[PDB]
Image (cartoon, coloured by chain):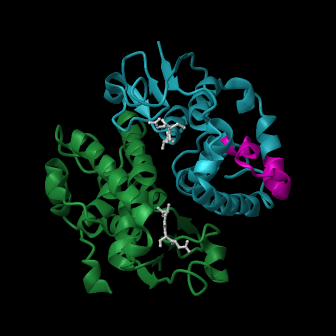
Chain colours: A cyan, B green
Amino acid sequence: SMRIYGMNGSGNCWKAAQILSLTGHDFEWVETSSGAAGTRSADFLALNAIGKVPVVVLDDGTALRESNAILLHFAEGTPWLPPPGLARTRVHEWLFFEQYSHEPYIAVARYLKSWLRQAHLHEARLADCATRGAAALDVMEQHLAGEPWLVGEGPTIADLALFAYTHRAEEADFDLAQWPAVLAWVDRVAALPGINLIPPLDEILP
Amino acid sequence: SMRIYGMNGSGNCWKAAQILSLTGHDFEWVETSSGAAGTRSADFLALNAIGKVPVVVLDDGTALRESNAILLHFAEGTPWLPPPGLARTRVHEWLFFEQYSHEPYIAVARYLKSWLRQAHLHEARLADCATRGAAALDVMEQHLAGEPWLVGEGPTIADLALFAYTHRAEEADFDLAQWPAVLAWVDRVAALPGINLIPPLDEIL
Ligand SMILES: N[C@@H](CCC(=O)N[C@@H](CS)C(=O)NCC(=O)O)C(=O)O
Ligand SMILES: N[C@@H](CCC(=O)N[C@@H](CS)C(=O)NCC(=O)O)C(=O)O
């Protein structure tokens, strides 16, 4: 039976659970810690040498890693992933934008401020995050002011990939009211059948 | 005719030029500055709101961005990219690992040290790059010690994506002799027909 190794509250892990649920796959969740008892354990590194969650393990033992690769793997042949061509390429562009220009600022600031509550250890990092995260939101705003979805005329895994952390941007100290087209898109994605939100970290973390 | 907006010496821009030449596409290179005269100019931001090179613009006006998306776009239907399935997923995994775990350390160290020659101004960051870049090479080494290519039995865009900066790792002060499987793989990729190396940055300056 299929397993997701993940951390409760993680947007990257949410991507994996969300696409599995959207595409009709049953799975077992395995709560995995950070460090020698989890992501840096012998057993885990045997699944993923990179030492990161999410990892999805198929009933045949195959271990899949990288949240955006997991989105691509399970969305293949569904309306969540266009076929090769311009639309698929536009999806790819947003997924690499997400990993390079968005996640490292939004997800990280949320982690440091609302998960660890270590704002004080990362003043420099956090100011940079605030600036570069705002720039990533500006890119999303510019696009979503003119089209309601990231690609083509309907939702795709590009929307899922950027929704993962953007829907919880308040925990990274971003006020989405200042990016009204992004806010409207967050609401549009949240209203889609089958989409679930990450509850507030304060309510799910020990 | 097709254009590539890029920076000479850039590994990410090399990915675009390299896949276009491997797949038989002629292109015009357009050198693009960093900042108001290039990547942050109004004309360039109209092509790519992210304000980053490479950008590939087709004759019909279509502007493509993100070096790994550009690899995916032009490799589709060629031996460089398998059709959907497990091997194709393995390719994706390496492309995301490259962007998240490898490029931000190896490409950035190379740029700050060997392009800008400002190592003295980025101490904490470059120490972090040295540590995390080494970890990324360890992942590559563990794989490549057991097989010659990143995915399956032959070269794919996974190899191209990782080769782009790894082949010039010496400019970020990584000695590839210390990762012998990665060293062997760099030579293996470099020997494929039509693969061109990025010239040393000291020849470009
Ligand atoms: N590029 C990866 C990044 C995943 C990632 O950063 N995972 C984190 C949690 S959100 C992790 O496993 N932390 C590393 C550790 O604890 O060692 C992806 O999108 O899957
Ligand atoms: N994820 C991008 C990264 C590209 C990138 O970092 N390009 C830099 C090269 S210096 C850039 O254009 N930055 C210019 C700017 O931000 O103004 C890709 O792979 O294409």
In the rendered view, would you say B130 is above or below A75? below
Residue A137 seen in the figure: yes
Q: Is residue A54 shown left or right of residue A62?
A: right
Q: Is residue B78 shown left or right of residue A100?
A: left
Is residue A35 a member of the stretch shown in magenta?
no
Q: How many marks?
A: 0
Q: Position of residue A127 (x, y in %)?
A: 65, 60
In the rendered view, would you say A200 is above or below A142? above
Viewport quadrant of the C terminus of chain A: top right
Q: Position of residue B98 (x, y in %)?
A: 39, 52
Give, as a single range, the part of the protein colored magenta. Answer: A165-185
Residue B52 image-quadrant placement: bottom right
Is residue A174 a member of the stretch shown in magenta?
yes
Residue B117 image-quadrant placement: bottom left
Outermost residue toward the top?
Answer: A1
Residue sitting at x 29%, y 79%: B201
Q: Position of residue B90 (x, y in %)?
A: 37, 39
Q: Is residue B47 shown left or right of residue A99?
A: right
Give the camera-side residue of A145 and B106. Answer: B106
Give the camera-side residue of A171 and A139. Answer: A171
In the rendered view, would you say A95 is above or below A73? below
Residue B78 seen in the figure: no
